[PDB]
Amino acid sequence: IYTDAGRICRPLLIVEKQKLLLKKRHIDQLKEREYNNYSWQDLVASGVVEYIDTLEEETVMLAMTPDDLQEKEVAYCSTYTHCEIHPSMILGVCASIIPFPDHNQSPRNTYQSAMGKQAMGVYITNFHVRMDTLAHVLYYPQKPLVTTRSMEYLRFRELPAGINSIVAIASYTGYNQEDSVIMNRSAVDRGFFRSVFYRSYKEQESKEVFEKPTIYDKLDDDGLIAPGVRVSGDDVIIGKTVTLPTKRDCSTFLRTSETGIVDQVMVTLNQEGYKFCKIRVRSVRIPQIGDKFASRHGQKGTCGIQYRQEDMPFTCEGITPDIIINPHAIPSRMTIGHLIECLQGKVSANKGEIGDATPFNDAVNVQKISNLLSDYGYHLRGNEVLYNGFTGRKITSQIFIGPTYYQRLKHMVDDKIH
Amino acid sequence: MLRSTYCLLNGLTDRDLCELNECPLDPGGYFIINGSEKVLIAQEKMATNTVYVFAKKDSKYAYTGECRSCLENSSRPTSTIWVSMLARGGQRI
Amino acid sequence: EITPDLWQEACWIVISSYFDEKGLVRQQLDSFDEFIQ
Amino acid sequence: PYANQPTVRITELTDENVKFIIENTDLAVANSIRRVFIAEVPIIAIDWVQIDANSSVLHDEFIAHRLGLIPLTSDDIVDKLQYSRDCTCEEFCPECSVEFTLDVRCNEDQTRHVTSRDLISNSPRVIPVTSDDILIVKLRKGQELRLRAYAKKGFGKEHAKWNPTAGVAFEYDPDNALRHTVYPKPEEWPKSEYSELDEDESQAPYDPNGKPERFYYNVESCGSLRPETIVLSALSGLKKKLSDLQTQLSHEIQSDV
Amino acid sequence: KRITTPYMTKYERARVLGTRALQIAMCAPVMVELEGETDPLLIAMKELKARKIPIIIRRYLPDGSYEDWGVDELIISD
Amino acid sequence: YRHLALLCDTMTCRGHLMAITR
Amino acid sequence: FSARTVITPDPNLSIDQVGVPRSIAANMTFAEIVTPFNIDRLQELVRRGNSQYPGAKYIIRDNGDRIDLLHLQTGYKVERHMCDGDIVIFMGHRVRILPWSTFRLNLSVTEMNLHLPQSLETRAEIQELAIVQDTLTAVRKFTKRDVFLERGEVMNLLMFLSTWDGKVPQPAILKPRPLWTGKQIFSLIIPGHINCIRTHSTHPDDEDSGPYKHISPGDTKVVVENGELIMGILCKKSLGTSAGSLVHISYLEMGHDITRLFYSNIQTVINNWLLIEGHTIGIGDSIADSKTYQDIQNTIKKAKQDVIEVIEKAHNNELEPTPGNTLRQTFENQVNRILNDARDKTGSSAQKSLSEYNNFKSMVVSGAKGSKINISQVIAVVGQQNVEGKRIPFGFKHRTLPHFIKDDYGPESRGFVENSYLAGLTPTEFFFHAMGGREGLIDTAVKTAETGYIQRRLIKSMESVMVKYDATVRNSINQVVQLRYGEDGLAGESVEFQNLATLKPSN
Amino acid sequence: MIYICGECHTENEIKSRDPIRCRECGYRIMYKKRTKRLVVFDAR
Amino acid sequence: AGVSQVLNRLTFASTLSHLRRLNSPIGKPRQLHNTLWGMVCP
Amino acid sequence: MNAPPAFESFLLFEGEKKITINKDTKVPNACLFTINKEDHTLGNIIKSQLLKDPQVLFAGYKVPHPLEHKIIIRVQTTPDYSPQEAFTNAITDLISELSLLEERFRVAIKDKQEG
Amino acid sequence: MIIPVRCFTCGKIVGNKWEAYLGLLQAEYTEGDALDALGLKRYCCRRMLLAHVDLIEKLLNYAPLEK
Ligand SMILES: [Zn+2]
Ligand SMILES: [Zn+2]
Ligand SMILES: [Zn+2]
């Protein structure tokens, strides 16, 4: 018997001889969770679900799913004492972002879990009031067209990090190497992954005074520039002078030409009562040809080159792909999970309902998605006839094009030129 | 620590959070030390008050029995004894 | 009494109840509450 | 060695899109017409923003980009106006720019939907396409947005903000008579909109002597320019570009000879 | 007695072209007729194939005995 | 084979087996 | 000294050329001394000033005084912003200035810093002393007999040949329409007069033994005569660097200086042709017909039945163990062999399923270096997951996962993934594959560090070994390592694989 | 110089060596307003 | 060392992952054990 | 500070010529036209119109670099027919083609309305 | 944050359709029927309108800096 802190456990179902303790009445009660005070604690106290730790896991023989393990078939094990609520719960927060993770290989899932930590997007709802250094906010975050039910509880749709873009998997002009991708310049002008980078500088004075020395033109009478002024390279945003026992200058520069526009200025008294200041400056980051973007399946990849809409290839309906990616990168960076995500995204966009990418579903496979896509006047396999942008010639090989969720990453040329 | 039972944000509605400049979706569970949001990462350690039998190769002991023991953080955070047996290369415990 | 072919919605609303009852950082909050109390 | 005789057959005429067919023409000219549709048709869009006050939850350049991405009805104003570098005036004049003024204050408790309808332009003939309205920003109580903008002349090469077309569906040879695409499974490919084949026959027989004619165009306007006006302006611009290239080539030839 | 390969090594070529280019960049007299192209490297190589480079190469044997070689008699495969 | 022969003769010309400098 | 920036590919650049942003180019300068026949251009640059890019920054007189940015004369060392044609090192590359702010290179041999030397001697010596699975597929598709190019397409491809003589070859077909062939275009790409024989990957061994041994029924062994592709499909072994390939033979015959031009011409022409022909990958490339899928499922079921029979016989344990191993090792070896051979057979069947149109086959037949297993996993079966060279260990008490029974040695447990990536992995298979991938990541992480340490140790071991002027190899302390390099005193990059033709044949 | 508060949003006057303290508000975290100078935002 | 670092506030998913993570005592824990099923994200 | 503005993509820089004619010495009766600040539009139509001319041996266009707004058009024609007048005839043919197309499009617009 | 104007792929106006989109959503109109009624035939416009996250209300929940 272990009652000490530290041990790790997960809650999961309790099974009778061959039946679950979870009945239809519990489901009905949980359906109207509000105005009924019937929460998960009541389910635990009802002897339906219980917490099993690693120690008890050896002594218990779990059931993966109740749909076809307690039924009557070729006998494998009839002493099912416990059942998992859902296998997809084995994944973590970052692993739940991947759609159809079972269709990928584990290195790709690990790589995407790493990428999602540095994926650019809105991070908190109150980013305006708070001042945290090295903050990135995306212009137009979007829900993925292909999502997992776990992401419902991660509040990803509440505030996401990434944009759904029309991605075609083609080799267009050679700027589409194993990692690089080529995006639509006109659509970037329309708002691909446009971001604001907030940087916060904190300064304190102590016995140092905030005063404008007699470039310092933008400085106010208080020694601090008012917010809303465009600051270029080699510019002073904070006017601080320290007494010299004629006066030494201890001002702060813009850290090697970090161009931007000052957003907010704050002055307050510290614990000692000395006045300190905080400057939040926002810089506009429009995706250049050095910014790195990653799908939910595939390695980190910089932008190859940006083509305008007329340069970009177009389908019979004039849908120029948002981003063209390397077909040859399937063995290297991205898997067929990316292709299935594109197919399900096309199906969801045509149908309207957001596609479900539950890892272990057994009811949403490639064939059903293909049939759904074919039902909407499209090729079942997601291929489409594309026309060359430069010459207008009909490309011999039909390009696989569909909407896919892409994520801008913190690694940018604008961040590292300074 | 944020969102704890002793924090001011405990038991606050969405409007209450979005009238004191706080994100309702913020999970909390972190401290604010010198204005910096610091999170304590659970450290992995060997379980206490349990007997483990191991077999080291280079060590002269064929089998070693270890048991880290405490009195629920009352004092002396480490207190372990070993019950080993010498290799015959006669089994002296 | 039984939930055949309806298992998906049942288990997902069960997970929903677990998550909106406890949360994501429930372990840290519970540990801190135990430490303080 | 000389020109063919193109024919234009318009099937659908609508305030938002035009569907037509160009016959007896080579593929490159049709592709260039599509290219000029997308990129080389000058329209008017807001390009100089000065925000006097912005209390909204959106930063200033967000509002500037949204304003610049709003279409403005410029069916006949583009011809009268001239480009900034082609105009020898001060930074702005009414002859090379259009002035817009926005001034909204949310003094009411409910959210104020500051839309393109609140954009007031001195020139009456050029206005946002609304006269639903293009939602610019949403203002909480006590939030005020005041700004002055100038809209200039430009085309899609400068920026996508000056793209007049919304969707340019360009097609040719709906049935693979020329076999420009090799379908691995032709039976599973959906029939084109302009396909003349029967249900049983998935693909047309190969035509060894065939070349691309009968290009189908579906040009959808964004509201800033009539699609027929879009096509006419595109043709005029391509003709002007070719005439300028003629002038430069003749000058260089007579200089070198 | 002068025993050594008659060819000129890649490293020898690199150093002799570098030294000749540096000299002619310091306005040393040039023995080959000049063209309109300006780059000192190009005139260095074109005087090289002209076979009138005014520098001999000393080749040090491992023991320490030198062995002079006029660049005129160093035939070039490339 | 030239590289392997050079490597082997480099650390066997001393008259006895020698380890790498490391 | 310099500014580091991420590298972005640019096919239009030369293989020896690097694209440098104008800002980084103007950030650091190259020092040049005044020459009587370059005074005008240096005067123009110094008149332009530091405000513009193609200018200069500092001037040093004969006395060493430094002047910031005006008379220029002999002996003045002025540092000017680097321009096109300069040499920089990270191997030296020619500098080309491009608008945006990223370094650009071609990826054909396989964030980083760059440096440009100041003195002319080091520049000259670096100048004199200093196609990755991407164009191979399009080359393979381009050399197909099916490739016929129209007059305009031929002209467009021809314009991208830097070594083109300007004479348009007569098309392979004159009537009814003038149609060229991709083989003709690549023949124009091939420089000089190269003669090469190289069997294709698809080329079976029975073609030579039987008839049609050089009329090539299945577009068999590649033959190139007089520097032009007579026949065959150019796969990786026939184009990539290897023993007696087209690139290798062309290099050894007439110089890397134009082997680089061969690379550039191949890349440009192939990219421009693929612009109209197009290449893609999608769902349909993993939907191999129901016949092959049923065959794969039947083979997997047979393998599972064989493993079950082995387990039940091992329970009856008559089953005399093989010598040199215990029962556990022998039976684990038997199970592993059964699973591995079943996986290999399923993968081979899946690869043979792709007849002509599958886009995966294009990479498989050409880039078969390490892509065969990935394709087999994608279509046929992921395969057995191994940890430490063995199946999944019993982490729990005699049980891999709590969802199985105790002492379960069947294929379902122990980490065999019956389903492929398309069909999706079961949660147990997903966890076992996660374990396998974690082991692979650990192995790669340790292997890279160990390989780097070994490389550093080895290069430090014999960094001072040099070939002396007496055709002898000596170290720093001047001991003769070898009387002649390689026991023959001859370079290792100018040799080839050959056959004696008199050692094997009988008397 | 006109200077605003943090929660009551009432303008306050702050001079040199003036402690940060809003009048009749009780709050001491506070902000400053926008500039009146000309600034150009390109609508690209 | 290795405990109580600044919270990762770059993404909400990043913040959630940082708030839910585990550090091994070692400064063979390299591999992923079978017992981590359900306990720890693989 | 590094990002190139959008106006110079089509605007002609001062001191640089719009079109430059260079004689191709290595092929008789051949020429190269370097046209600055132009995309694939004019190059493509000019190449197609030149191929329409049966008195040309070679006719093509190239963009050496997408980032550099410049096109190289190679024209090789028959003897007693220099590429210059071939280029002039092709561009005049394009102008006449576009004029006729514009007139017929106006006629079609008139017919479609109130009809 | 707010509904984009001129959806990125093709450029069709979608910034004036968000409010009508929500009005149709509150009605019996389903997702696909609402998208068709708004006139977004191309699936890029449907992607733009469907996947959009309206963070503007969440941001406006906080009190403004100036009253
Ligand atoms: Zn004017
Ligand atoms: Zn106050
Ligand atoms: Zn659209």
Image (cartoon, coloured by chain):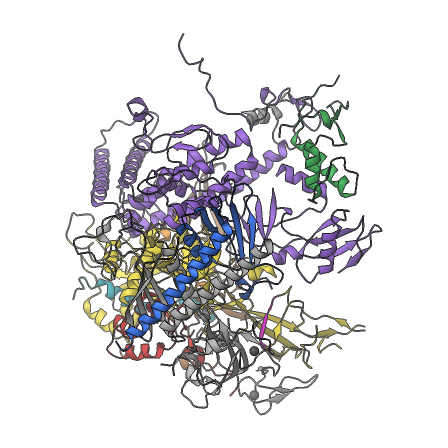
Which color is chain E depicted in?
green
Residue extending farthest bottom: H24
Note the chain letter of the blue one.
Answer: J
Note the chain letter of the yellow one.
Answer: A
* Picture quadrant of residue A248: bottom right
Residue at point 48%, 83% (across, down) = K63
Which part of the image, by quadrant, shows the N terminus of chain A?
bottom left
Residue sitting nearer the eye, A401 or G334 = A401
Query: Does the magenta-highlighted stretch encompass residue F16?
Result: no
Which color is chain C depicted in?
cyan
Which color is chain K depicted in?
red
Residue G392: image x %, image y %? 34, 43
Residue extending farthest right: G63
Q: Is residue A302 at all visible to an observer of this figure?
A: no
Which color is chain G depicted in?
purple
Q: Main secondary structure of the magenta part?
A: strand
Residue extending farthest top: G507
What is the magenta range? Answer: A258-265
Residue sitting nearer the eye, D70 or A258 = D70
Which part of the image, by quadrant, shows the C terminus of chain A?
bottom right
